[PDB]
Amino acid sequence: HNGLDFSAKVIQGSLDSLPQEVRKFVEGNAQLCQPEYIHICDGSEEEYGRLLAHMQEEGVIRKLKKYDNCWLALTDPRDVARIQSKTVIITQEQRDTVPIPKSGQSQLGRWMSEEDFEKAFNARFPGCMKGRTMYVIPFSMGPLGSPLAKIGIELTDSPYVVASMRIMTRMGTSVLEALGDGEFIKCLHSVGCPLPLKKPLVNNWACNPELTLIAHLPDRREIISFGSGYGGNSLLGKKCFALRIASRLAKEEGWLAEHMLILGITNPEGKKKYLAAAFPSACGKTNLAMMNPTLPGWKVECVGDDIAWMKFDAQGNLRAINPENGFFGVAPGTSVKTNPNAIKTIQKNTIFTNVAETSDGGVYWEGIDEPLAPGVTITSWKNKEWRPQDEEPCAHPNSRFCTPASQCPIIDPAWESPEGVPIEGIIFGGRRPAGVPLVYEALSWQHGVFVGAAMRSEATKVIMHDPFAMRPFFGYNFGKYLAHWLSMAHRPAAKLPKIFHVNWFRKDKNGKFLWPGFGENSRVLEWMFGRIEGEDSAKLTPIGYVPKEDALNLKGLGDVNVEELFGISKEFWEKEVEEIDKYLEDQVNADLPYEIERELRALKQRISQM
Ligand SMILES: Nc1nc2c(ncn2[C@@H]2O[C@H](COP(=O)(O)OP(=O)(O)O)[C@@H](O)[C@H]2O)c(=O)[nH]1
Ligand SMILES: [Mn+2]
Ligand SMILES: [Mn+2]
Ligand code: NA
């Protein structure tokens, strides 16, 4: 007849231009999802501007008239976040995806059988793009033609995803030319609202919360996401690819894909080093990644604020790239005070989601610390006039900026270097109101892997385990991931970074933070820097090395309560090790490596002799 040829529906580009396997992915899914048109994205400025104005004319976004090319999306309140409960990974065997927990409920991932997924898929995708354009987004995670970069193709029915993916990845025609006949991750996305609409459209924001499902199929190199337009559910390069699929790839291939910022720190003498840090969301990665140091002569430069791909090179340096092309940061809390470098970044060419709008076309959120002129009013993220009298924030707590990384005033000159940046330190941390000192240093690589494994952080009151800040993101069995980290010591050449753990959030008996934080965290970074150099600035404790007395620069800082801030209590740490023991036994068990169990035994013994 005319085959399975969708050429007649192509409104930009050509199916004949596509590499063979890309064409097959596009056409097969056009046959399944029945889009009205196919738009192959070129990544051009013209494409982007027109798509924005189109969304503008449909009421999907508003233009923010105060700024150079900035935009505002307000969502359906049912679709406001990446949703872990609807997030699953498919493998033949459950144990390959998560360890089998002794308690029967795993905190370390959600598995679904191939059978169950096929039924779920068939219930969702057939005809799901009826009446819509299927956009084909060819994208690079990493600098174009970096040896560490990986290519994806995302099919989506959301122009919001297209625009946001232009920022957060490298996308367009240059990627298709770079890809050629190579392998790529297949990323399928639908908002799940075929036309004609069966359910009312809320806030011009297409979604299907009842059928929302974010699936990963590592053995097929597929990510298939249905029903949410938001964040990590729809922007498939970010979590789905650059952590969940990429952690699996990394394990197979001998590298690491982690939930880590990469920042550069320069002393007053001009001396430079790169550091990576894994904190859970809402524990300050973006802030640290673009920190404005208070300590004079110190400089911080940003490589990435969220994801790090790391591979030992043939010299044994741990090379890291940021696979992202932008920051997708939580907007609330961002002020000139807390994060001035973010604020300079987001003044132009930025897409805001679920933040408030001022009457003069500006953006507003909790913690912005920017007084408004009398007469200037605020429209909340729910499209209502808002005042601080109300018992609701003007912006959703998970609201966002999505901004190009290149616009960061302190973007590192090597942030796109195809070889990556050499990592000399790896920092773990989160929110611990009690017990855990400002900073310590792991005693060995094995100890450091244990420190990552043991991470706990206040929920954003409950304290939960979040190993390596990867709890939401492991692409495979966490015990095996532990073994993969430990295996890095068994290769000759590898120059293993020093591992540290931090805590900004230690609080006193009256619930006041014992440490100021923010730009004062440069004093902790200072202590860390010297240690990589070999400075004799450390005191041994049961948990690791801490700063020696007077080793931290507290100058310009008045009287910080250092005794409480560095206190290490036998009673706290004996409870700590017991809790950790029971967690690893329950959640990891048969897959817990011998070396991590040994480190737990060693820590317990050192605490017992306090
Ligand atoms: N008290 C305190 N709060 C902080 C510090 N760093 C970040 N925060 C707060 O933690 C919240 C999350 O910051 P953010 O950079 O979004 O964390 P991310 O989600 O991990 O990238 C914001 O409300 C920040 O103001 C700190 O050093 N001390
Ligand atoms: Mn962030
Ligand atoms: Mn993150
Ligand atoms: Na809207």
Image: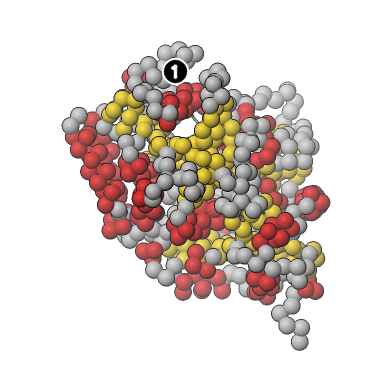
Quarter of the view holding residue 293: top right
Q: Nearer the viewer, residue 186 or 16?
A: 16
Depicted 495 relative to depicted 1: above or below: above
* Vertical position of residue 242 compared to residue 94: above or below: above
In the figure, is residue 542 to the left or right of 420?
Answer: left
Q: For numbered disc 1, what is the local secondary structure?
A: loop
As shown in the figure, which amino acid type bears the numbered disc 1? Asn
Q: Quadrant of residue 425?
A: top left
The quadrant of the rendering that contains the C terminus is top left
Q: Residue at x 58, y 62 (%)?
A: 185
Looking at the image, what colour scheme do you see? secondary structure
Tell me the residue at 57%/59% (across/down): 209
> Can residue 486 be seen here?
yes
State the residue position of label 1.
Answer: 553
Residue 346 at x, y = what percent?
68, 36
In the rendered view, would you say 45 is above or below 191? above
Tell me: residue 329, above or below residue 292. Answer: below
